[PDB]
Length: 5
Length: 103
Ligand SMILES: [Mg+2]
Image: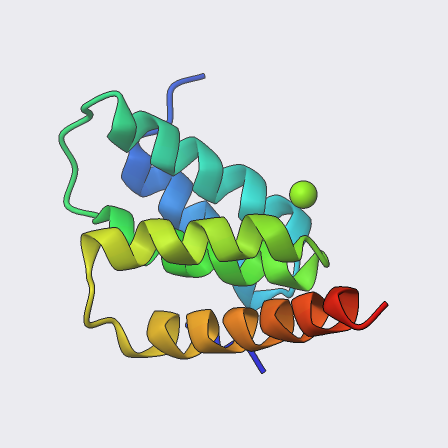
């Protein structure tokens, strides 16, 4: 899971 | 016409909030290009890269998302989400390499 803003 | 880097960033954020990752990448890349050519602006490259990396990941372009994450970390080594993203991408890459070395 890559997190974004 | 002429949009400022901040204009592009704001448009990028509208696209991002609509889950339009195609237009997020276009606007954010334009903002980054204008910053890289030395436009004076209150937006920072790190926030632009944060949205851009996420948008590119959504598009399935993992190599580009990794590159953008590394670029972000060069500018802000302590960024929490980018550090998390990097460890994820490195895990995936380590898995792929492990696979190649057994086959
Ligand atoms: Mg793309």
